[PDB]
Image (spheres, coloured by chain):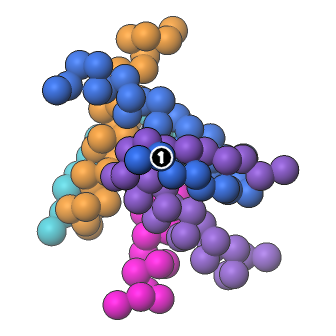
Chain colours: A purple, B blue, C cyan, D orange
């Protein structure tokens, strides 16, 4: 049930944040 | 500065989880 | 602008393959 | 074993380039 991941690095977070965002978009076009 | 990012993806999270642990190891060598 | 990247990891490649297709999708929606 | 992945992005490539180099380093620690 969900997995919280704390990232101390601001850059690293931005990366995963971009992947998480693009991942959610794929779901919209992949049910 | 830590950042909590909740993700509902076992694979997606596993990715960032490996990228976070891999990025921390590189710091030990880098400067 | 192209950069041929050769890797001996079927798993690692599969990852970037998903990230590549996910990046093109998010880029198409944005501008 | 090899998998040539043609990338058409300087940023995207830089990402996989860091993930590829970071993955190879893990092999030295884990095996």
Above or below for C17 versus D26:
below
Q: Which residue is mark 1?
A: B2
Q: Is residue B30 left or right of residue A7?
A: left
Towards the viewer: C13 or A12: A12
Residue C8 is situated, as x and y percent measured from the top left of the image, at 39, 31
**Percent of width and height locating residue D12:** 31, 60
Rendering quarter of residue A15: bottom left
Crowding around mark 1 (Cα neighbors within 10 Å: few <14, some 14 to 19, many 20+) is few
Q: Is residue A19 left or right of residue A5?
A: left
Q: Is residue A6 above or below residue B29?
A: below
From the viewer's perspective, tell me whether residue C20 is left or right of residue A25: left
Residue located 34% across and 90% down the image: C31
Residue C30 spot, x, y in % from top left: 41, 88
Residue drawn at x 49%, y 61% is A17
Give x and y (percent) for residue A4.
67, 47
- Along the line of sight, the residue nearer the viewer: A26 or B28: B28
**Is C3 located above or below residue A5 in the figure?**
below
Asked whether residue C8 is in view, the answer is no
Residue at position x 25%, y 61% in the image: D11
The residue lying toward the viewer, choosing from D15 and C14, is D15
Q: Quadrant location of the C terminus of chain B? A: top left
Q: Nearer the viewer, residue A29 or A17?
A: A17
Decide whether residue C24 is among the magenta residues: yes
Q: Which residues are magenta?
A: C17-31
> Most extreme residue toward the front, as rendered?
B1
Left or right: residue B29 compared with residue D22: left
Residue A10 visible, this angle: yes
Question: SS at mark 1?
Answer: loop
What secondary structure is the stretch in magenta mostly built from? helix
Q: Which chain is mark 1 on?
A: B
């Amino acid at each position: 049930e969900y997995f919280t991941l704390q990232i101390r690095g601001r850059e690293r977070f931005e990366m995963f944040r971009e992947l998480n965002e693009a991942l959610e978009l794929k779901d919209a076009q992949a049910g």
